[PDB]
Image (tube, rainbow, N blue to C red; front, side, top):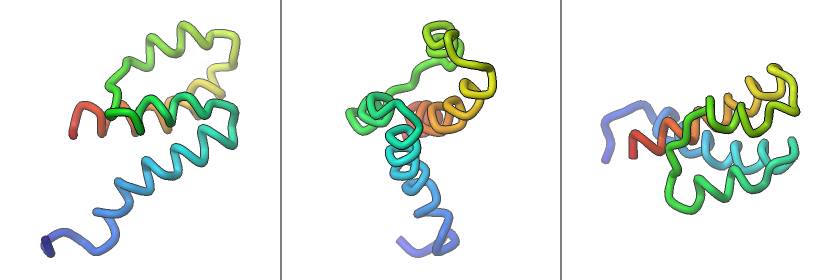
Length: 76
């Protein structure tokens, strides 16, 4: 399957593995598990409402991984 750049094809897979390591190191090993289950396509406006305890900065940082996961979840 040679066609795309020999790094971007893996950048999309490290965007899942680094989300596992990031979500786990940050405080949320469950969000990684939810994507590693079957790539779950949630709305950030749902998890933002449930984690409204945290700052907008914590939600934007969490949203960086969750949006990346929720993105590959709608895009296979």
